[PDB]
Amino acid sequence: TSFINFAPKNLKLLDPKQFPQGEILKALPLLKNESKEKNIFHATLEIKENHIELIKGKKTLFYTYNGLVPAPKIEVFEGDKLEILVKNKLKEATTIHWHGVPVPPDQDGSPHDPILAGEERIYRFEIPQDSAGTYWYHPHPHYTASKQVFMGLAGAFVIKAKKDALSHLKEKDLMISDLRLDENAQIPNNNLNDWLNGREGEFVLINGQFKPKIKLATNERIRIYNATAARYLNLRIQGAKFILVGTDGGLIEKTIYKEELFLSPASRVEVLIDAPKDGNFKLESAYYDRDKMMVKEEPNTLFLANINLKKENVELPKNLKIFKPSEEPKEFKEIIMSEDHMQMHGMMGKSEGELKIALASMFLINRKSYDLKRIDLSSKLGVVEDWIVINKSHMDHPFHIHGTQFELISSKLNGKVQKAEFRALRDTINVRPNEELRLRMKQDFKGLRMYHCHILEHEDLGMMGNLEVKE
Ligand SMILES: [Cu+2]
Ligand SMILES: [Cu+2]
Ligand SMILES: [Cu+2]
Ligand SMILES: [Cu+2]
Image 1: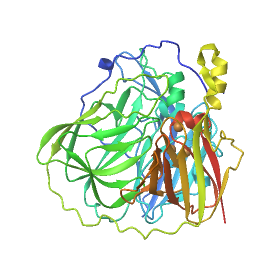
Image 2: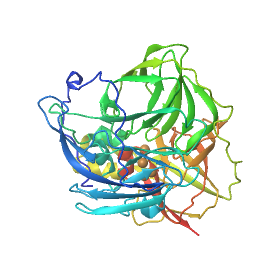
Image 3: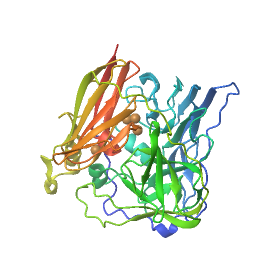
């Protein structure tokens, strides 16, 4: 439990007036392709500490990809062949997980295959047909994923089709992260509440920028990334609506119109914005009560950014994407997410050391904590399965499974059933307290996969298991 560090008690945080704000939103920098061959993407990611003059007077220590905040975006096409050299220049082990991207387990940066401090690894994989979607990359080492993210390590990863219903549209990225700064402009350690609830950095950023001015138009294909450790968003633009056109694993069948867009941690969508006319709007997130513990919160709306919106009509087809007929499942899995508050009650009498033990045995899957060495579940290569994911705890947890996209079939809550509102492919899904979800998927590569809560602090505290995929 040496990975559990608590911030100083009554740590004072930075005054938000000191944080640069109100700037025009910039596009993410792209990770340069070192190769000139057709359909070949070659590049290098260095993972390193850097000191950034963000707050006047002060240098802020970040962990970065290629020394950049925000990180370089990877953008490739279906059918491309990728090779990325990754150099770990941190003083601790790390990995890169291509979150949601269908790659073989040995190319996917799980805590089984760490990159030690001072070493390097090459990741190599093909971009499959039909994999167009909106993904991201971030660390997944044992125990320290939450700190490495909160230090700055998260980047965009997009797979494009050579041609699809929206591929002629100009694109925009709204990559949403969050950042905590102390009174001396440094990124502090988690406190107890962050470990219990998942850490939410007070400064919520879009492409690394605080309260920016965004120029958008209604004929743009906008990718939105919830790249936070634990923050639930319920996005809205009063006076406008979202036209949902895609989820993690790409386009959906038909436009879905939404006044609010719920985006739990690690989820991504593609949207257009609809409004009747040109205008100036505000991007906000409505408070979502996720039953955080030891916190009484103001149910406040979070303001994220100003949007200057240009109205341009755009032709949208009747069908965005033709989905394959749903396949029949042949085996079934059950995932129970739960918590043990045996200990933690009597918070009052515990030393720092005993809180750490409590935290480490608290967040469970199928009544167990993560064991790096234990195979929890086994599935057959290429076989369609339904996974029944149930949340028996008092608080939301977003479920993630590596290696595949799944389709929500149906959900149940409070003794009632709701069939999915539309077919979509996701790799991460919120599970409400007492809710039961039915998720259809298959695994197309042999080897080990994890599945876990994607509130990063819960994952690091053991809310995770191992899946073995065999022939
Ligand atoms: Cu992830
Ligand atoms: Cu993942
Ligand atoms: Cu993971
Ligand atoms: Cu959780």
